[PDB]
Image (cartoon, rainbow over all chains, first blue to last red):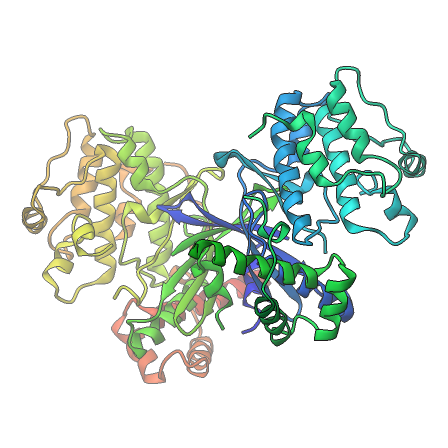
Length: 312
Length: 325
């Protein structure tokens, strides 16, 4: 009765699926993905934080971010109906290029990645698990898109390995730097035999850039992969870096403000939606945290300004 | 209540594939879902279809699409089915503007008739046999039958006119098996000519050609195949050929020995009085039909979800008893 997705997706005739409409028994292009998350392997404190984190995602809308169409809750499991790509992930593509992509082609992929996270960070959305495996091809459209937002050692910023309190936007900037490296060398920037030996390198932040990599692009990598989260680069620097120039709007939250009746409506709709206790919402917004509340606030803020500009 | 409704009928989008992905690319682990609309259906249609679809779950044959699950809801009915890679047969035949080579027709046709042979012995008729309902599992070498004509339909009349028997165009009572036979003859004809045997500009004159049963076979088709076709395409259903004859026509024989595998025991093993009664009692308890209903259907020798559910439950009893042997 209430385990119908369960018998479809987990039954004996067989967690990421494609649902594709058939025509005379062959695939068409009407398709969505479905991701199945195992609630059981998680606590009710953690399972409560997962559902708020993914509900928030339905509000993200960007060409280079994979849309979350629905979340369907179950006792035992959670189902995400997602946009479905065409040519696999960006990690297998790099495996097909053992010494790197040509820089002009790299630029085209990385600009899209950076444009995506740059949009996220202006809306207080933050990926936390940024890997080439989470960059996905939409080949028929000529796009890459980020998927599988957060909530394995190479991609982790070295502060994450220390366990100390993090500034979440800077960890994405690091994970951005590991991605640039892998595009232009076809190898991860920190890889030794022992998982332990590796860890030292990442803490040290000692990597070699191959000689064929241009002077500009070498500089961009050192601006994102520095041992200290405070010295890394904000996105306006990366977005406008020389290396990315030439490669061809921006979120309204960045340069316009809410009216006070507009601001109050959001916080009212947020509490009525059981997003959080109003006190927590204002601590969050004032602390300027990077979590599903601020994100919810700022995505909803953007939908009102977008409507206000349309009327004009 | 509506979780499936949102998956398949949601804004992001009835026959779908559900396919396992691995690093965001398709695999071969896949099933299919056919969605059936129960609205615009009375209560007795909705009741039977639920048992027909329910009894198709018991059919097992290499040449029939497996019906793994049924999932009933208020509006829609969801059939979890076996998914092919290959397309259907009509698109295959259409690619062959002058028919398939006769020894390839033979390979496909022999498979189709083993499917219909297994069905008719277990008192299952297709009622909608046409090359669109023959699917390719070309990774496994074979074709399987699908979309059995269930109570939703009883493909529309403008389209299915070509494939329809004269007696179901005239509209009177009929032997349902003989209708599948007529449909076998039309398929064989398409396999070896890439054209349907009755087709005209007006769909009113096609109707006449079917009633009079006039068609012409290209010269290159052998005399035996030609003969098989005329034994399945008679206007009188009493004149057509039962599956023993068809399945043993020289065109498909050629004298190798026959495998007992994939043949229903119900056709040669007999049942005891206590077992016969044990089925009907399980059927009455399972609320499939009145005991009168069941005894009447078996006495009249009908082909529907009662007699079929009877010979399927029977075959299980025969298969387990044979296992003990």
